[PDB]
Image (tube, rainbow, N blue to C red):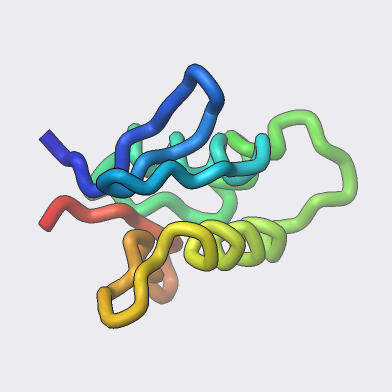
Length: 96
């Protein structure tokens, strides 16, 4: 019943209310794994292994960078981020 964000696989974008937000391949995959694992904290290692499955020369830092790309496109001013940072554990999307 979580509807703050709704994935659109037809054009692999995400809807925030009535706003459709275009996402790159990596941004979509990263948002998808977090949403599929709602309320569970995903470590950078877990996110890296899922979104950069066969990539070479890609460290955990890239996960952090993409979380920032995601926040830039989906977060709204005056509202807490849709993706929460959990120091020492990773990232999580929490149903409120």
